[PDB]
Amino acid sequence: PPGPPGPPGPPGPPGPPGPP
Amino acid sequence: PPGPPGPPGPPGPPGPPGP
Amino acid sequence: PPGPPGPPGPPGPPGPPGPP
Image (cartoon, rainbow over all chains, first blue to last red; front, side):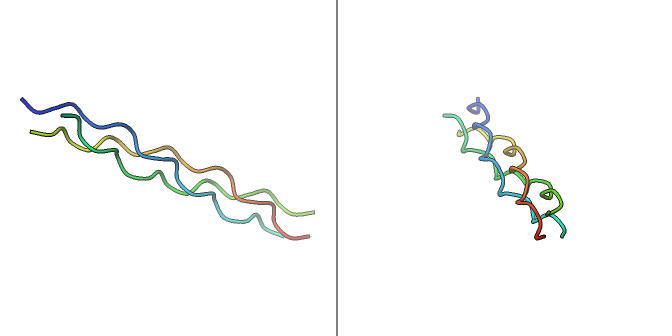
């Protein structure tokens, strides 16, 4: 049989700047 | 063998308003 | 055979504060 799933991916980048 | 890591997460949410 | 890729990473952190 196939091996198991790999681990989770890394966290995404920061979100965008807030508004003024 | 185990598979590769999954993909990057999405961007986070917006920062807060400025001063 | 190799397992499949893992699941997605989590969201990134919040963006920075907006300008004045």
